[PDB]
Length: 383
Length: 94
Ligand SMILES: Nc1ncnc2c1ncn2[C@@H]1O[C@H](COP(=O)(O)OP(=O)(O)O)[C@@H](O)[C@H]1O
Ligand SMILES: [Mg+2]
Ligand code: NA
Ligand code: NA
Image (cartoon, rainbow over all chains, first blue to last red; front, side):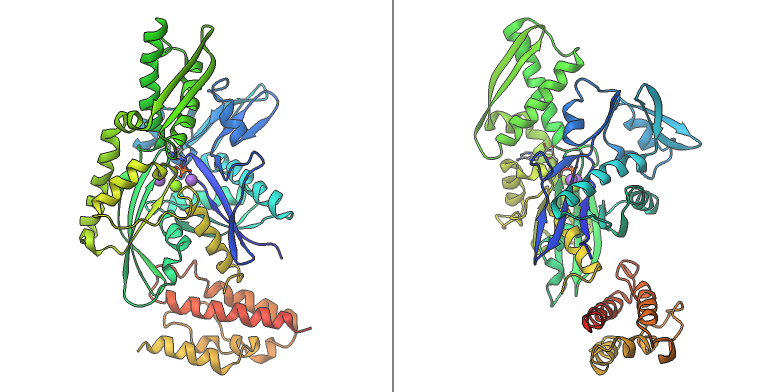
């Protein structure tokens, strides 16, 4: 029967892969993207998911939902939930001790549990793999951060069940990445692996010891509120001042213009990973005024200097909690979309004294890649 | 040398991918501590329906997901793997 998939169900973007014909395919959505925003837009007519959801956020901020992974498996009165709520433009309420996302859908107020919201994203990733395979998808492996507990794991599984999936296993994101590189298929003495995962909202360092295919999380570190979104924000403020200088207008107070600027900054940011400058081009940004401008890689790097270099403290921290020296880790693996930033890679590599990084698998894809490998073995479709 | 591994290695090769032979003797290679698996006799392994029924049961016991972080993790996967290949070979028959 039909193959099983791997789904990286991510805080900011999700990704799906299938292991078929001896190879893993990370599957593009219908807009051409190999990853998909973990975004759910509610409107008067439709429910939108992914690229279509994220693109209308500027117009529809209060009914566009993201960061559900931050609510999943948590109680309303969890200190993390209470602080996170400040950032979000959508509403969060208490149903009997459980967090609910409250939105306006089809001119009626509806509320959804975190695992329900994540089910919708999982559903979309399910559809992405079904469009590609030309057949229905049921079995999945889904990934979860190493530091997730049993409540968050169970709730992630339940989001699978709500999506129509039979979740074969819930596995750790760092572990899946190591599997993506086939590090668990090495023999001999125990190897130490370091996972450097910098995504859109979270930064994770994990150290694993692998021996005879068996993983052990030795230590974890990072910052659950540090990712690409923050580098975006540095550029956003950079240009808010620039628009104020050129035009004597301040856009800080206009939700729509600020978001529209973030979207251009994020696109610009990706360009800077492969090129040394990027142009920004927004029609009628504010009160009729076209914004056109340029930004160098150097300028991007220095706008983010502190955030980039502080990325190494969690490395050192995980390294001591693991009771290992820099020289003692055998594999470094780059995970997360923000690790495509050249200055982050030099920064990490120079910390390890020039040692080569595992980066050939697209970092924002390495998790789903490993989950797909695992789904296959779990189904008897690999070796 | 790993004695619990050596016993599974020996079980695997002695039964020659006979799904029924493996299923009917799996209790002699499960880790000490395993409590769910009641031994099957050939008598409940005659029809393909029976063999299907029992293999799904065996696969649940030794499944690699449940066995993660367990002292018998490696052996569960050794068994699961051989079960899957025995079953695929059982299904090729015909
Ligand atoms: N080429 C690139 N250069 C810089 N940042 C990138 C690039 N590609 C993706 N990103 C960023 O990576 C983040 C998403 O990372 P990803 O690992 O896909 O998601 P998640 O954090 O949800 O796991 C976003 O901030 C995105 O802007
Ligand atoms: Mg990630
Ligand atoms: Na992701
Ligand atoms: Na991350």
